[PDB]
Image 1 (cartoon, rainbow, N blue to C red):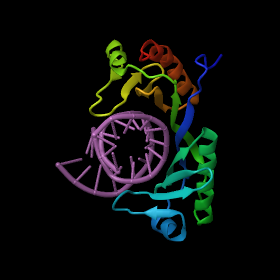
Image 2 (spheres, rainbow, N blue to C red):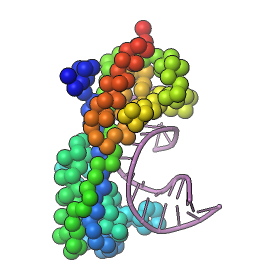
Image 3 (cartoon, rainbow, N blue to C red):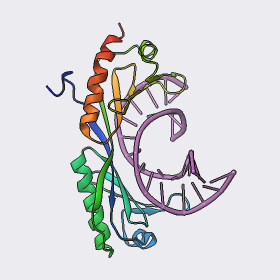
Image 4 (spheres, rainbow, N blue to C red):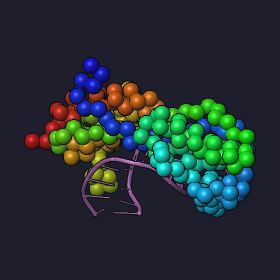
Length: 184
DNA sequence: GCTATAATAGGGCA
DNA sequence: TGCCCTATTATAGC
């Protein structure tokens, strides 16, 4: 009823941001922390990681923080919360302001090969397929505004969503098309 | 471990 | 001002 295709895209990566609302001393965090990495000349953030939920945090001097790698939105907020407390314990008056899911990446397998060239040709205003550069067809759906990477194998990557239902809807919108161009 | 995709954050530079 | 800096993640042919 929500997934007429019978297939449910698996969530693979969630990118979120949160505002710790306090400037941070990155050199102090990098020295005091254990799971930290800081190379100012390369990137302006402290890169930290935890095991559960398995994620990576990018902590900036401004107090802003990016959390990547989680398998769900809840897992992403949970992870972000642990990093916030890690930073709190380090001495800073960190809070958890304006948490937001910025991107959801999902993937699935329709279990049948696809004729990418024919698909791109019939949907040129939406498709970008150049095998010699990247083996996947880049499908830029407008409603919802989502990008799908369609491979000959039947495997699909769906990215750009800020709510999981967009991920699901884009896949459901694309399913009938993939079937039309099933490789025989 | 590069190719390409989305999204975020910051310093640095043409 | 734009854009790459970095890390994430599925995918696949090089």
